[PDB]
Image: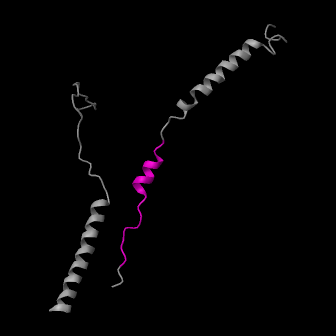
Amino acid sequence: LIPVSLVDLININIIFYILLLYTLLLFFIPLFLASINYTYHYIYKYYNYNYNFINNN
Amino acid sequence: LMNGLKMRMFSLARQQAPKIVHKPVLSPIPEHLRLVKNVAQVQIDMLKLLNAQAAK
């Protein structure tokens, strides 16, 4: 069979494929990280320090 | 609703501007400020009474 071949085991063409693929991955990481979570919105809205005052009398 | 039927009617009209609904927003800032007001008025009455006592 064709895919049963030692030439296709260390094929430099697929290595170029992998190289270009992961270089492009590296180039686009800062866009994959650009998703917003709404957890600090929750922290801002719900974190309420104690607003009661001290009154000895 | 009709005899032997139920249906869902949807209008067909362009929405030129958004539809507003008054959903009041809960916030503690007004009550914070009103508490500050009340405590300050307490202290002000206290100072006035103490001045009246010390001077009269």
Q: Position of residue B27 (x, y in %)?
A: 31, 57
In the image as oriented, which residue stretches furthest toward the front?
Answer: B55
Q: How many discs appear?
A: 0
Q: Nearer the viewer, residue A32 or A4?
A: A32
Indicate left or right for A48 with A6 as reference.
Answer: left
Indicate left or right for A31 with B3 as reference.
Answer: right
Up/down of A51 relative to A10, above or below: below
Toward which corner of the image does residue A26 lie, by quadrant? top right
Q: Nearer the viewer, residue A21 or B50?
A: B50
Q: Position of residue B20 (x, y in %)?
A: 23, 40
In the image as oriented, which residue stretches furthest toward the left?
Answer: B56
In the image as oriented, which residue stretches furthest toward the right?
Answer: A6
Quarter in which the N terminus of chain A is drawn: top right
Quarter in which the C terminus of chain A is drawn: bottom left
The region drawn magenta spans: A37-54
Residue at image position (25%, 73%) is B38
Toward which corner of the image does residue A5 lie, by quadrant? top right
Residue at image position (48%, 42%) is A37
Indicate left or right for A32 with A15 as reference.
Answer: left
Residue A49 forms part of the magenta stretch: yes
Residue at image position (47%, 39%) is A36
Up/down of A46 relative to B14, above or below: below
Q: Position of residue A18 (x, y in %)?
A: 69, 20
Q: Nearer the viewer, residue A2 or A56?
A: A56
